[PDB]
Length: 217
Ligand SMILES: [Ca+2]
Image 1 (cartoon, rainbow, N blue to C red):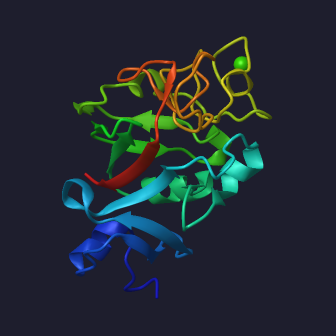
Image 2: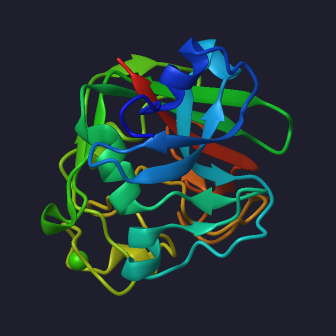
Image 3: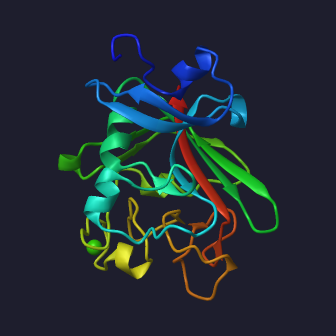
């Protein structure tokens, strides 16, 4: 129950769950949620809120879809903005982004803190210092931006970034990263509308794998 249950994947790691997989955690208001724990990468204890791997799931979705979450525990998913807010509300959480290209290269980026606000604040990103990683830094430029989807434009562009770049993100005008973009399978001719992390592979290369995950700082 909520009284003794784990709050996140680090609690689960501490209790001896050493394999990655789906486990029940209890959010701050006691709402139970099934989450994916990455117990392997970089010490383990990471709660995964976004996964792309094969293009099986459509990510070009509306506000309601991103709010509640969508996809599959067996594959690709977005955990949901209400869930991500709740998970990052208590304490301080570090963010790790893991990427794999189509050539087999693994790259990563790490940030010292990560929070998303509530729906009233349009799931605004509150991002701490870049730590490092082979992927470089394509998220700091998104700090303090609201989340936007195709049907709800909260970006700082005269354009509709989510529609123009075919994703959903804390778009500014418009992006350095676009991990909820189209699954375009490596090099693409269209500009900046793929699973792009521009500090590493630029605006015309879409990654094979994306994983976004959090753990107590
Ligand atoms: Ca706009």
